[PDB]
Each structure stands twice: as C-alpha cells, then as structure tokens.
Amino acid sequence: GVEIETISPGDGRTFPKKGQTCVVHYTGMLQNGKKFDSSRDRNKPFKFRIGKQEVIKGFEEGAAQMSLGQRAKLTCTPDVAYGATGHPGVIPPNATLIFDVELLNLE
C-alpha cells in the first residue's frame, strides 16, 4: 500500500516511465521514530532508473505515481520493504516507513 500526500506544486503530467533514470530528493523517516536516511546530507540526489527493482517496492510504486516538481509524502507498508526481515542495525522488523520525496528528475 502506497499512500500519496503531495505538497502541491509541480506539473502533474511528466510521469516517470520505463527506461527513465530519475532524480529524487528523498528523506527517510521512521513512524514514531527519528530519521534514518537523507539525500539532503550527502547532497548527491541519487540518480536511479525505473524497472529494475533497485529500490524497495513501496518506493518503486510511489516513484511512478508522481510528476516533475511534485513533493509527495510516502507511507510504506512493512510487507513491501523490510517488515519480515528488517535491515540489520538500521531497520527493525515490522516497521512502517515514511518518506519525504521530491521528484526533480531527468528523462
């Protein structure tokens, strides 16, 4: 389950498609918890493509459901990313993820 809560401005039409490498100012947030990841710190805004299952499933579907300039707010279910396993030391098992995602991309 991907929940989209968009801070309004953007264009609403440049949708990410297959074979397109897109650029995201992501920011990780734990529900009832602190941050765990941020592209704002490293300031290299994570050039990644679409259709290769590089990222987790909750962030993969939320990437295609945005457009250029938009600033959404993801709510990733545990079963699509880490809720059974848990990323070791960083993500506990059964964790619901929150992301600040802005799509300022290319292609």
Image: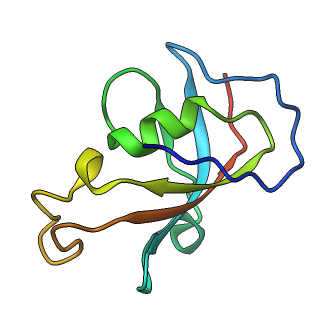
> Residue at point 53% right, 39% down?
62
Question: Which residue is at the front of the view, 73 or 51?
Answer: 73
Quarter that holds the C terminus = top right
Quarter that holds the N terminus = top left
Residue 78 percent coordinates (x, y): 28, 56
Q: Quadrant of residue 70?
A: top right
Q: Is residue 89 left or right of residue 60?
A: left
Residue 81 percent coordinates (x, y): 27, 50
- Residue 6's place in the image compared with 94, above or below, is above
> Residue at point 45% right, 44% down?
59
- Residue 46's place in the image compared with 96, above or below, is above
> Residue at point 58% right, 53% down?
45
Question: Which residue is at the front of the view, 57 or 40?
Answer: 57
Q: Quadrant of residue 87?
A: bottom left
Question: Which residue is at the front of the view, 56 or 97?
Answer: 97
> Residue at point 50% right, 13% down?
19
Q: How is the image coloured?
A: rainbow
